[PDB]
Image (cartoon, rainbow, N blue to C red; front, side, top):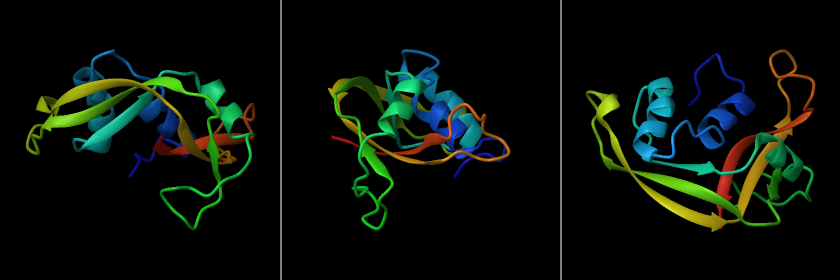
Length: 135
């Protein structure tokens, strides 16, 4: 579920690339305030958006999440990341949700697609739209 003002690529960048704080509880407030609920888990890749776009250029592979999709690509190398896990759910006041954080170095598989014709910049014809899995 993504807010209407975001294209899938912009939402991917907001959820998985732009960690606004090195603390999960603070970083997650952005995502949660946009989604209007506390995400149970979320992974932030400590890499650049451009680096992910390059991964879209790697060979196509089956998405481990949706075995019916073939628009996934393997990162090739490990990247540092931070996984946030909800420790304190608060369905009445989402700004009070608290998260644990786990640093790691792993590979990732991303799904890519053609850019949003009207709203995504022409600079990147192919963009990441879903973080399918970290291995």
